[PDB]
Every structure is written in C-alpha cells, then in structure tokens.
Length: 257
Ligand SMILES: [Zn+2]
Image 1 (cartoon, protein in one colour):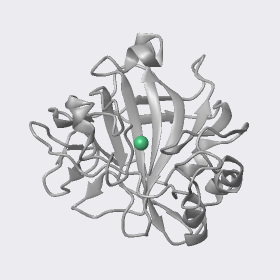
Image 2: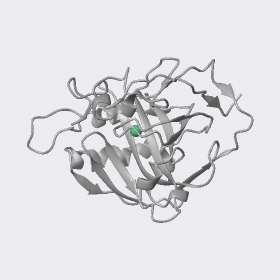
Image 3: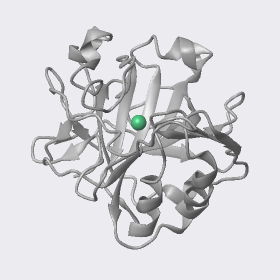
Image 4: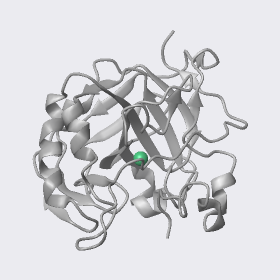
C-alpha cells in the first residue's frame, strides 16, 4: 500500500490514485513575488476557545490529534472561505533532518516540518461527504523551523512515546491548539488537494506566512515515531511529506501587502 518509501512513495501514488496528476494537486511551491495581494479577502477567523481534543492516534503515516467535531466548537471562517469549517484533527509532516520536512515550500525553501489543522465545511454534514466537494475542506498550514522551543507543543511531544507504532492511540483531552499558532495570521491561499491518498481535490489551502519555532529536542521526538506496527522491523517515521506539485492553472493569493 502507499507510503513514503522508495517503492511506495509519492512518485508511485498515481497508479492507485490517478488524480495524483490532476489539475489542483497539493502541495505547491509558493513563489512570494508572484503571489498577488487580494484586497477582497475578508479577515481570517480562527475560533478555537471551545475546542475539545479527544485522542491522539499513530495511523502509520503521521499522528493525528483528534477533536470532537459533532458540534461547532472549534471553527475556521473568513479569509477566502464561505461558511463554517469544523476542526476535525491536526497532524504534522516532517523530515529526517531540519533542512526538509514541509510539504509547501516558499521560494523553494523547505521548512523542518509543517502543521495541518484540518477542517470540514459544515454545509456538507459530515467529513466523508465534504471530501467529495471542491470546497469541502479548509486546511490551515503552519511552517515549523528549528530554534526556540514551542511551549504549546510540549504536551504533544511528551505523549509520542505512548503511540510509537501504527494503530496505537492515547487519550489526549484538554489540549488547546491556540498554543500552536504564530503571532500573525497573514497567509497565502489557493485551491488544492489532500496531500495524502486519496489526494481528493477538495481543499482550500490557507498557509500562514509566519513559521512557529520548535526546538531540536521537540522535532527529534517526532523522528522517534515508527511507520510500522508493534513488533515489526523498525522504520522511523520521517520524511512523511509529499513534494511540491505543478501549479497549473492556479493563482496563489496573499492576504497581506
Ligand atoms: Zn497534512
């Protein structure tokens, strides 16, 4: 099945998921000089005060911090979005070394990792229906660089030992995702896709310009996770990122001048 290895990685995905070569695939390189300020964008609204985290799961390709999305508790609105999008989970993509890991790139620069807060459009009722629609998901993407520790990330890092292998989960209640946001909400936006199979072209991407800083020790702990299940030969969970895909007939818009 698909993964990030030599024999099942991103360059193979198109065989099972032909949309991999589609017209609005993600991630992309963000060329900062070509992105155009769009005065029509409305202010972005990240409302996470009532967020209810539940569980953290190693799914074999990342770890997901899952939220109660059975009501409007943690929602993304505004910006390029019409309507209300409910937070369902966040996860990261990261590298084997600090010089790679992000999916989006900025003027071809790769960051050490990239955080994805995944939200679905409530007008479609459930996540499974939303992913079948061109405006079904909104993902807030945030770059991670290595430097000072991110205090609001530490509760995540410290539970990783308990979900080392594929299929393991742990209770993860009362986690506040506001502690993972940078100061500025300046962003780039474009229409794209899931970056993992099934690669559905259902996402409005909102990628923040300002990275957050995490420490070397924090990202080292990401890299101790395993793609494999318990008892199986160890395959460190690293380089679980898809590279930049052709922009094709798309324009990246900036929220800032
Ligand atoms: Zn992702």
